[PDB]
């Protein structure tokens, strides 16, 4: 056993490793969306910038869990990062909807992680999740919902003008 | 259902709306106390400033809960703001005692809100309450208790000199 | 009687207390509109900012009347602040129309207040209303009319693009 | 009963007083280690500085619990601060191991305190512990483990050169 | 024997260790007084600040003796720090009187230490005491006497107004 | 066909997608090495920093190829990022040797890519590889060889002192 390990259940350690993979997976999904909007036949560079920024932030989420794993004396076991479920994200509105779905999935995993930590009476892990992950997810989800709402109201994805104007005035 | 709503029980949504009303109500009570001390026959302008500042802070408390409600995809339903239980707050000491009683009442409502959130396994809401409301209430209550203690020890409310000197050296 | 009270009719004192309530009521209506536009399924953040600013200004209007009441030696009697007549304000254009209707109602109350002051030969109160309230209302009404006109001309509320572009270029 | 006391169980109050003593005790242990390394026949001044800094921080931990006790309307009852279990700490590596053991003991006491607070439904106290104590302990423990690991790998305590070089390059 | 030890009698070494304990004990007494005045039912925050500052200075006194012990090649042996003789210090005036009594007790111990050093012909130790401790004690005692005198003259402890005004104008 | 596509062979497009995956894979290998050195039982924080920096740079390498793919009108097809071939990298020296092996493997893939581009008479792609990738690889390989050489000469991995001193003076 690790000399630092204290009050850290094997189930929590394993769930942290799963969450690490999920954060890396979200990073990769966002990377894919980013460069979809960089295509010459899509050409929405603030959509591309927006999702590249999300990609880098998801990598930060993963690295902070990796630090946590070592902080608590657990051991990191990395798994493959699955490639995303689409190569072509169809439209700005469709991508924002896919991102919203993704962030809710990550949120559900964080909430189960918090439930596990509390069930094992690991208040340090529960507050780590509460402090660094839960409100970030709520804000992320709310922002994505706002974007989806505006794109739909503007007439996307039918209206190429809607996405162009959203790219310029909201994401730019 | 809201596209952002996740792990957010109908009971929590309703309790948030009640808390919104209570924060607006505290704001109004403090507004009333403020301008009581602005009367020409009371004339304690640092008591007036102190409670006006409390009034504005309580409005901030309310707006942050309103933001939370929308963040979680609940729906805000406002209710009347009841006028306070006094028009004339009698003295500086009496007002500070009324405020202490008020802040303990708001604190009890926040603690029941936290209990509800935990009972519904809503760690985001529980930590929101813990992070932004619980210690603010404890500090508020301790400060009011300190003020009450000093006013009593100085001889208030009998001693008009006591309240005047407290207004100058503590609240000014 | 108050030691400061001079040339201040009981009817004026009572009308000031009514106006205080109306200003607090306008503040609450604007607060409600603000957070309607903060909903994830409405998502017009400059509409939300615009009405939050109106809400804070209406609170200032109320506090200045409260100061006036004490300045003249009248006594403040607060009443409940009624909750607004809608929970859901439907659209940016509908909200601006509701605000226009509200500001005309507040203006009519101020004009009756001025008429009362003049009928009681209270030139200090009449000029207080003229100086701090009447032109502010005229400017408020003109601004709201301008906004309504532009929203209608742009195609609101049918056109979700109209409100989005107005939010960005006029209110942002 | 204290006029500020709310939702604060007698068991929590007593456990806070015990924790106060333990924080003061850790401060004293670190003070002792500090001046052991200041001996002319030990002479590791960055080890001495490192543990003096820990000593002062543990005193801060204690004072913040004392403030908390008064914030919640409990009453501070101080007990003797026991002198440490060694007068001579043998080596840099041995001291770091003793510190690691100490910080895990303080951590176990904080975790039992958190469990008590949650069992008494005192979310303010639980979040106080989570916010100000739990991650500080995890970081402290991880740092001490790192130091122990490097000292062992360098050949301490046999190798006087190892401790000297660690003192210079890690602690200096 | 220590390689640095020169002209340093075993009796002086032992008396230094006793003085170390007494300085740590004074620090703890002052810590206790400090947080007594932080109680919501005492609430004199400049009394609290004044004694917290004394507490930190007494810790400095102790650390400088610990440095001296090592400087002269003696060996530090720490003893328990006894908890103070009161939990409740009754009033500002009573605390200042207890502090005055304490500082005279520390002064008597320093004067016996100086007498011992001179009797063992240890001019370095005698001048260390003279230079760093004796005038500090005389100034401390004179200051405490001044405070006691003013509190008594103002009508403390009967007069809660006296202590409040002293806290504001002398200690603040 | 893409409206921008010119002189860009299907084989080059496919090889670019393979290289994208390899750069992402190198990034992940370095991420794994980084947090291996962050373990409490390894504890070489400049080794950890060194490989984290390599990880971020490899992600930049990948993103620049993704930009290139779109610049030339090819289409990005992402594949899984395989997890690295070790979970535990044994020692600083072993990790540096694994990195050296990795960078030579990436270099061999870049050289085959350049050969392909030249065989298809794609001078833009050949010079892209020459300009942004080939010398970076040569410098990377030379640096890793230097590090390996110094670690071996210092006595790593047997000598825990060697890796500690290298971490401090070369990587820090
Ligand atoms: Ca796969
Ligand atoms: Ca697929
Ligand atoms: Ca009513
Ligand atoms: Ca009533
Ligand atoms: Ca009503
Ligand atoms: Ca209605
Ligand atoms: Ca005029
Ligand atoms: Ca003992
Ligand atoms: Ca012993
Ligand atoms: Ca928390
Ligand atoms: Ca004892
Ligand atoms: Ca006793
Ligand atoms: Ca695989
Ligand atoms: Ca394998
Ligand atoms: Co464990
Ligand atoms: Co995100
Ligand atoms: Co994430
Ligand atoms: Co529970
Ligand atoms: Co739900
Ligand atoms: Co308050
Ligand atoms: Co509040
Ligand atoms: Co009159
Ligand atoms: Co207005
Ligand atoms: Co108004
Ligand atoms: Co209680
Ligand atoms: Co510590
Ligand atoms: Co501590
Ligand atoms: Co000697
Ligand atoms: Co002193
Ligand atoms: Co002293
Ligand atoms: Co071609
Ligand atoms: Co590289
Ligand atoms: Co590369
Ligand atoms: Co050729």
Image (spheres, coloured by chain):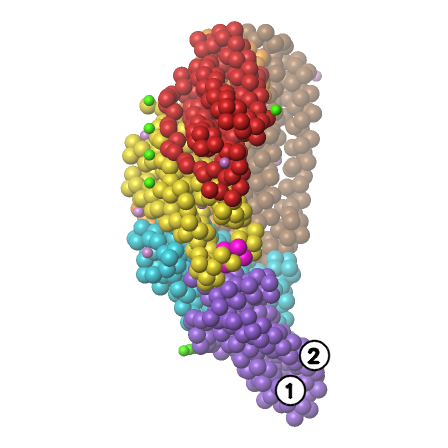
Chain colours: A orange, B yellow, C red, D cyan, E purple, F brown
Does mark 1 have its CB less than 8 Å from ligand 30? no
Which numbered circle lies on residue E131? 2
Region in magenta = B162-166
Nearer to me, D171 or B47: B47
x 47%, y 30%: residue:
C12
Q: Position of residue E170 (x, y in %)?
A: 60, 65
Cβ atoms at labels 2 and 1 below 8 Å apart: no
x 67%, y 39%: residue:
F142
In space, the residues marked 2 and 1 are separated at their CA atoms by 11 Å
Nearer to me, A75 or F89: A75
Nearer to me, A71 or F111: A71
Nearer to me, A153 or A47: A153
Residue B110 visible: no
Disc with the residue nearer the chain's start (2 vs 1): 1
**Local secondary structure at mark 1:** helix
User: For mark 1, what is the residue?
Assistant: E114
x 44%, y 23%: residue:
C33
- E110 sits to left or right of A94: right
Q: Position of residue F87 (x, y in %)?
A: 46, 43
Give the prevailing secondary structure in the magenta stretch: helix
Q: Position of residue B163 (x, y in %)?
A: 50, 55
- F95 sits to left or right of F128: left
**Local secondary structure at mark 2:** helix
């Amino acid at each position: 056993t690790s000399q630092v390990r204290q009050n850290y259940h094997q189930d929590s350690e394993a769930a942290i490793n799963r969450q690490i993979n999920l954060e890396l997976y979200a990073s990769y999904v966002y990377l894919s969306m980013s460069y979809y909007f960089d295509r010459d036949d899509v050409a929405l560079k603030n959509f591309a910038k927006y999702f590249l920024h999300q990609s880098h932030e998801e990598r930060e989420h993963a690295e902070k869990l990796m630090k946590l794993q070592n902080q608590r004396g657990g051991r990191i076991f990395l798994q493959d990062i699955q490639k995303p479920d689409e190569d072509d994200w169809e439209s700005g509105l469709n991508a924002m909807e896919a991102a919203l779905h993704l962030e809710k999935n990550v949120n559900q995993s964080l909430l189960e992680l918090h439930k596990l930590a509390h069930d094992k009476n690991d208040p340090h892990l529960a507050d780590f999740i509460e402090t660094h992950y839960l409100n970030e997810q709520v804000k992320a989800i709310k922002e994505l919902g706002d974007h989806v709402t505006n794109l739909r109201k503007m007439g996307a994805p039918e209206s190429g003008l809607a996405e162009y104007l959203f790219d310029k005035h909201t994401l730019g």
